[PDB]
Length: 409
Ligand code: HEM
Ligand SMILES: C[C@H]1CC[C@H](C(=O)N[C@H](Cc2c[nH]c3ccccc23)C(=O)Nc2ccncc2)CC1
Image (cartoon, rainbow, N blue to C red):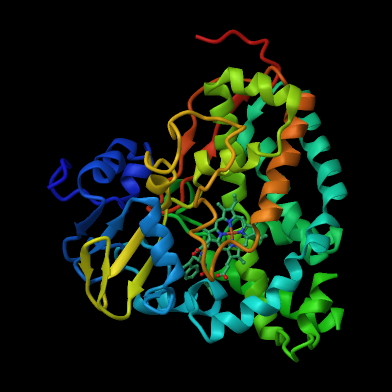
């Protein structure tokens, strides 16, 4: 029996609006590393199956991620929490993007799309993203103080997506406005936003992009050496998946990496001098922007002595796995030189491992270089405001003094 409150649910958005449940994950790793998280009827975040297995250890997250024949992404999608009254069809519509497909459909799409994430493809974005990062940090520093999320974290992930796709400069504002409405949450600050309508507008825009382009886009829509290509429709769903996979994730890694530097000033001093490229992985481990994704067992499977049954969901808590005391040396220390760094912030190794990981790391290293260049003495003004979501670990706002000159308490 682990020591938790009765009825505790690790996917409860009301927890994450205030804090990460770090103590509770540490209790599970220690005492019940695979634990049945029951959910009362009508309180399952859109799932009506009585609860899920909480997976808290890094080795178990890797084993589930490897065995995608047993642990399905398609069956229930991979997001483990929606509003409790969501219609089943709105969970199943996720199946149109590759993250929520199984083999064979997933395998074909992943092989085709991997073309867009070659070393050359990602490297071709470096210089424009470096220039853009420099101006973002300089403009924020010139403002003196402001919301770090909006003025520092937000723009570069969006420009990385826009650059990868070759989106015309004049269309970036509208693309960014759709993208910022599309990853749903349950936060009252965004309750009036409709993610469906924006997703639909982005699909239309992308299908036309495919029509007109007829960089990475040409490669994806033309037959490759094994004869495969995206239809315009599949290209539309590919663009939607980038808009949701690569926006708030990287953005939250930037905000929480800065929050870590503020908490660990010796690491920030070391970073500013040395700018180690290993920093990006430690920032992703520390930030764990996706707290959890799930799978559904398609057959009975014994996982580390626990008998998972056909049809049951398993929720991989990357936030727990990334602090696994058996894997990391002193996981509760932020160490920008950590190497190796076998974190699962981009997933456990397997078929769905984040295809954007190198682009995310480049975006993170470029923005931190620019922050070091333009605002080396930044200090926070007030505590971060966290996002109400049961699976995304988000920071909505964080007021900072970029100059470090204002008085602090
Ligand atoms: C720090 C930022 C990021 C984090 C933490 C993150 C995390 C993840 C995770 C956890 C998964 C699922 C892995 C699995 O199920 O094993 C994933 C998949 C994916 N990510 Fe990322 N990601 C980030 C940035 C990006 C970026 C910048 C892009 C592209 C612009 C991107 C594109 C994708 C795509 C297309 C998938 C689906 C892959 C598949 O299903 O085969 N991600 N990411
Ligand atoms: C046409 C169809 C609409 C649903 C799209 C989708 O799956 N969006 C969901 C959030 C979500 C889940 N169910 C939905 C229903 C409507 C609108 C949004 C959602 C989403 O934001 N997913 C996500 C996955 C990985 N990383 C970050 C975010 C894929 C394309």
